Length: 186
Image (cartoon, rainbow, N blue to C red):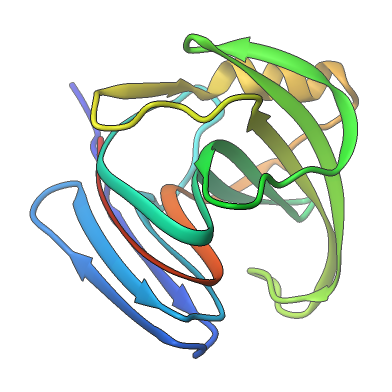
């Protein structure tokens, strides 16, 4: 009675080298060097607002800007959302909307806008929903993101996810950096 990960996520813009590894089960690894922008992770093809995402990042060693975050899309409306648990040399922020406490940590709530940006609908103009942890979360242990807490928190701030749910992964995103990570998601 557990529907583990079924979607392998691997996107790059071509900058640098991104050696992403689809490993056994819900485990993946990625080492990247001097890259552009990339998003690699494992998750579910259809995200759920009521899903509790579990993960264990045995390695999350970004040398520069890298994210260890929940990442997913919705359609109608078109929205790209984050739950950033840890990062490298840059903490993503935006328009402050409030805070939410979940899974032992307090996350800041931000909204941003993407302009003529790639999406699951192509080049579009869409809103980004962010929940960014105020402190970096410790890795190497079993961690859970109770996503229904963030969805309710976003909703209480006028941030409403779409009705159609595309993928939803525990991702490693980096930009203009090098590093490695090893994560198991279920």
